[PDB]
Amino acid sequence: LASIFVDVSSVEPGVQLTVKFLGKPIFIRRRTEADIELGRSVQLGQLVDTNARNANIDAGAEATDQNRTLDEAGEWLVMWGVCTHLGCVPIGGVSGDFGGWFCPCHGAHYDSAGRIRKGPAPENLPIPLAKFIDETTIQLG
Ligand code: FES
């Protein structure tokens, strides 16, 4: 019975909701049109980590923008807010050099799809088991 159910009905574009799950933060960002476009503009060959790190799809899936969001429209980016270096909480609100998150502990930069682009972190921020169960609610777990 671990699953939790997050009401995202009030999350506007450019807002991140942070919820605690299994003791750690989950970031739920409703991405802006700029975030989405920028995420879709990155070639796989440009990425540090080409694996989607996404619990919801094949473990060998490529880290395309489309394989990083819950929805086809790419508005809903849900990920563990746990830096893949040493587990600090990355700072969002379009921070760092790649329009995403910056981990101030040792300077990891993640892009607008949560993919690692610069710094000592080895992997893209992982995506939890997560799905919409209706228009307004994301089940985590
Ligand atoms: S814990 Fe994030 S860069 Fe080291």
Image (tube, helix red, strand yellow):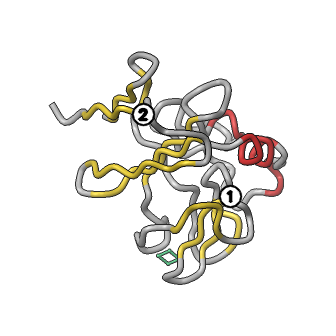
Q: Is residue 109 above or below residue 31?
A: below
113 and 29: which one is in front? 29
Residue drawn 63% across the image and 43% down it: 31
Residue 14: x %, y % from top left: 61, 48
Label 1 vs 2, first from the N-terminus: 2
Foreground residue, 68 or 45?
68
Check disc 1 and report the residue beneath it. 111
Residue marked by disc 2: 8
Answer left or right for 91 relative to 137.
right
In-image side of 5 versus 90 (left or right)? left
Residue farthest to the top?
Answer: 134
Count neighbours of disc 1 (C-alpha within 10 A) and say few if under 14, some if 14 to 19, many if 20 or more.
Answer: many
* Element on which disc 2 rests: loop
Rendered view: 69 above or below 101: above
Residue 12 sits in quarter? top right
Gap in angstroms between the C-alphas marked 1 and 2: 22 Å
- Point out residue 57 in the picture as x, y percentages from the top left corner: 52, 30
Residue shown at the point (43%, 26%) measured from the top left: 131
Q: Looking at the image, is 30 positioned above or below residue 112?
A: above
Circle 1 SS class: loop
Q: Position of residue 122 (x, y in %)?
A: 58, 66
Please give the name of the residue rendered at 43% of the width and 62% of the height, measured from the top-left corner.
Answer: 82
Say left or right for 23 vs 129: left
Check the picture and name the quadrant holding the C terminus.
top left
